[PDB]
Image 1 (cartoon, rainbow over the protein chains, first blue to last red):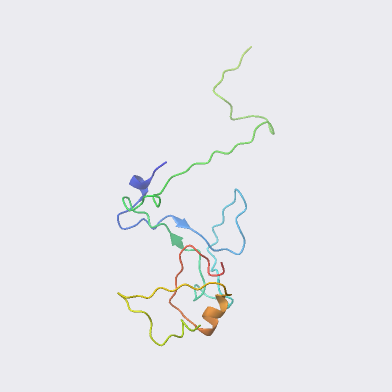
Image 2: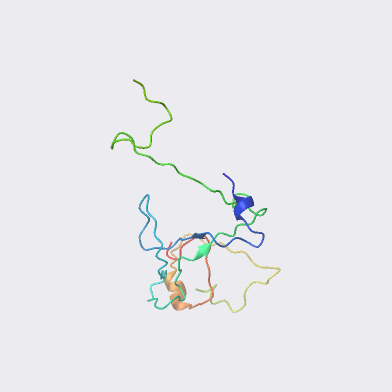
Length: 97
Length: 48
């Protein structure tokens, strides 16, 4: 569902980070927060940053009215496993004699 | 390499558009032979 009116700024809300560059892909249901310098070029890259080195620091340019398809959407994915372990979080349905 | 080595480039208001096809291109040699420092790319990795 839409979150432009609560997240987007007129000047651009560059607070929500997204990363494109890493040596290894992301396994399903996993997160990585190591902001290690990524060297796109064949040359060695040391220190904080460098040329031909694309660090994983880029954020959304979220604007309220300018965002049509670029508009932020706040998404919640519900994932569950059934009939593998004893159930704890159960349905509203009441027990019987 | 030649369009990187052109004496005079296309005008601002009268930019010339060009298309090439049916050859082999590499990005490593592009910044090896013709070094640059001012470059940022959208939607594509430099290696991609």
